[PDB]
Image (cartoon, rainbow, N blue to C red; front, side):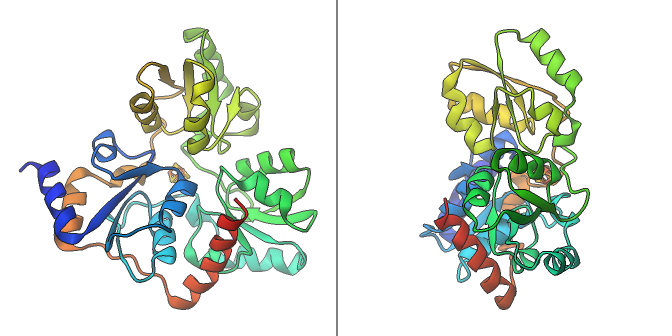
Length: 299
Ligand code: SF4
């Protein structure tokens, strides 16, 4: 079976769009209608004319698309496409922090459950966390789940950051070390380093640019050679966008298992079977939607 041909036909039959994250397998990126980071996928979720969304990404991302498109069918091809860091944050963490700091806005990374977003004042992604936190009317904000992004936000805004939970992090980005920075500079001495803010702070400090994957794409025009400190499928994405540049993985083994639960075959099966339908309870969705819409307004 020609999976690509079958998917193209089913997209037409289902009036479906495929939205893909930047960490998707190359063959999935190649059949997606739109590819982007967390923030771009959320905005693109607000101008969907199609009836069905196939979300080639992890669960919290498909949930966000469903919150913004409650009357469209949102399909996740595997329920094992999940984010380890997003599931570190529970409602009880948020409520405990709200108790200690009732006047602190609750700022939740989009890497969170819809249930957790129901208790947020505003959501953020890596691309807009600093701008959003800067503009909130408070010198202290509750922020999670990623402590490494928390550190970056604190450094850039000067505000006091109350992490929820205590040790939230992404195992993929925590793989990068100072030895990887030293190896990169030795193998590719003419390259600059683009580093995701989910990397540990001492690695962040070695960056030529700190950026979300979306900002990596935006700023890649500033140099012709880059070592890429994020999930390794980002190198494919950058190479396709800028064939005239050179991109090298900082670590080939920087692999997100949840992202790679999505396959060409189960995208085909997703459209064929109309599964797995993503649903968000109306009251959770209403409250999460308020925080997300406020994020999109605050840029
Ligand atoms: S890369 Fe890390 S933060 Fe992003 S989805 Fe995978 S586990 Fe979650």
